Structures are given as structure tokens and as C-alpha cells.
Image: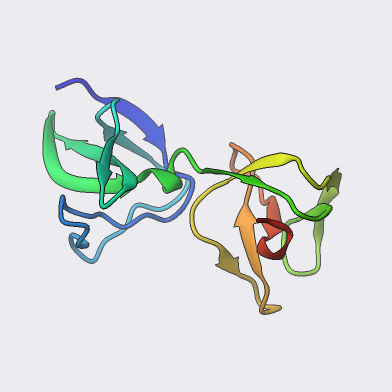
Length: 131
């Protein structure tokens, strides 16, 4: 079957066609998985169907961990590499659209951050700056 390599942008569990998790393992960022090119919808959410050993299997990865999610900033936001370290001097402005990858991360400061940027760089934005 036709397969395409997709980079995992956020630690992703495997799910079956019933939105229930498959196994205890998880594919870690930023590794690559082979999936079907066209996407599918489970419970309204977008998924990729995993291809293993040349055949499609009952394993699905949430597309938010591959394609991400286009979000709009409601505040001006800095780009962070950790809780206290700034990643650069980029200042994202209110109204700009940014793609975030996967569920938010809780840093050690207690606040929650979104991984941004289609790359492997430690670039995070506070969730409180979105919606």
C-alpha cells in the first residue's frame, strides 16, 4: 500500500479506529512514522492511519502531533526555550497565526507552553497568549 513518511512533532500514542489507545508504547518526537497519505476522521478528530510492514494496520496517530494546529495569538508573545530562558528575540504579535504541535507542555514553573515551529528547535509559546 502507498506509504508516506511523516515526522512526529509531539510524543504520540497509538489509537485504534475506536479512539482507544493501542499498547503501552509511544512514538517520540522527532522520529518518523510511515502512514497513509490521505487522512481520516475519528470522533471528529483528524488522524493518520499507520502503515507497518507494507500494510495498513488498526493504528492511528492524531494529526495534531504531525500537522499541528493553526492558532491565533490574543497577546504579544515571546519565544521560550525553557521556563526562564528566551529562545531568541522574536516577538510574536497579537493577531498573528502560529502553528502549535500537539498538547501543551507544563514547564517546571507551572505554566503551560506550546511547541511552535516546523523544526526540532526548543521554541515554545505560553498557552495563555492564544485564543
